[PDB]
Length: 60
DNA sequence: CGCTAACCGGTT
DNA sequence: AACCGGTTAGCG
Image (cartoon, rainbow, N blue to C red; front, side, top):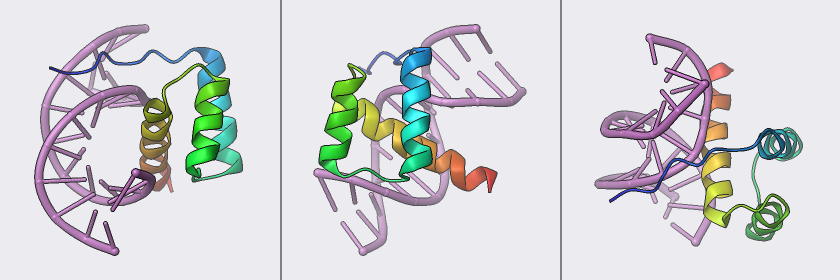
């Protein structure tokens, strides 16, 4: 038992990245706000950020 | 295979 | 609870 892999839209990717470039971490409220803006689950966004930070430490 | 979303166990 | 680091796994 495992969740389907989410397919982010160009719009979702773009806004997630934009948010990352602005803030490296999100407060719970900032997360919920972003999830609501992009029609995503809180956890999808939480996970995105986390994986994005991982990528960020690799590439620096 | 490369990129990356999702999961697990441990850190704090 | 959130993050981290390592791991598994979907898909172009």
